[PDB]
Amino acid sequence: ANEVNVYSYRQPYLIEPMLKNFEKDTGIKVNIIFADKGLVDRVKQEGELSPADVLLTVDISRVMEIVNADLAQKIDSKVLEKNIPAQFRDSNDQWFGLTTRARVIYTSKDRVGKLPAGFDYLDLAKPEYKGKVCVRSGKNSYNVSLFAAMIEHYGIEKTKAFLEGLKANLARKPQGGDRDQVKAIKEGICDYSIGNSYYYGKMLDDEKQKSWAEAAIINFPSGEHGTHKNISGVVIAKHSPNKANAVKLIEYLSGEKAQGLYAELNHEYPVKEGIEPSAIVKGWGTFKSDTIKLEDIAKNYEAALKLVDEVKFDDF
Ligand SMILES: [Fe+3]
Image 1 (cartoon, rainbow, N blue to C red):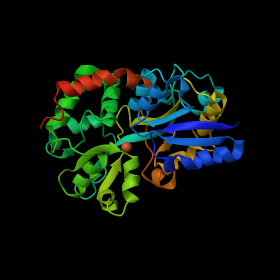
Image 2: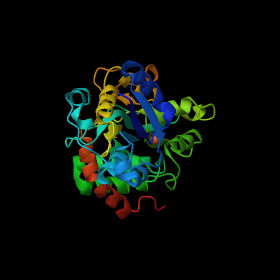
Image 3: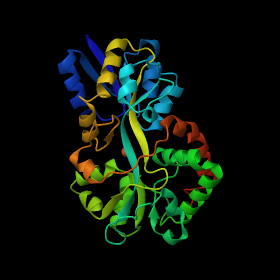
């Protein structure tokens, strides 16, 4: 044992409970380094001497930043294979999803209500939604990843046409984050937004923002390819000094002792099949998740960035 060093983009309080439980079960000391927007630079600068064991981050774009900075090592683990569905881990064994986040469509509770069953992201590009849609910058990773999935499913031409239609329907210049779009729904600026599911929980947890969530309905797209999921996950650092402990830790985080808790704390979904979401998350509804591999989203990420620039999505 001795220890394991977790460099985390995610705030320590959102990961500490499961790490404390791991410590109790194994006797392995878990050190948390809050690398924040750090994280690649810090580990790269620390180089061969870096104590980093587990790199914990959020969004496939950040996972790819780590992999593409040559900071990952390949891990062969039957536990990770069994616990994590293949779509939420690397076929090339360098990264592993631990939770998912759904990119959903929020609607005005009063002015729209629940979306009809069958509603797709694609429907937001239809002319009837002109002036009614709020989305943050198209270059934001949450959106680029969604568009990358669309490239996989539909190709660049159809995705480009979608982006053009979506742009045409925006109520305002893309601005702010996902929560800001729901604030805009609350204030009647728009009736539809795209945003991550977990924000609904985060807003309800906040005294000011709860009214934003209360004015909106969370809708899980239910077209052909269902609801887009992105991930939080982990990578074992290239120069991990406590590799065995590190692998033990991520195996633990992938399993039934940690999955429910970790997802619950973050209002996310567990990756491990059979683990329930929290009561609050479950209450938002059940839905079909896209089966697309996150590595295929990563593959199309650059093309999606290119398409966003081509259509000048943020230009109003
Ligand atoms: Fe977020």
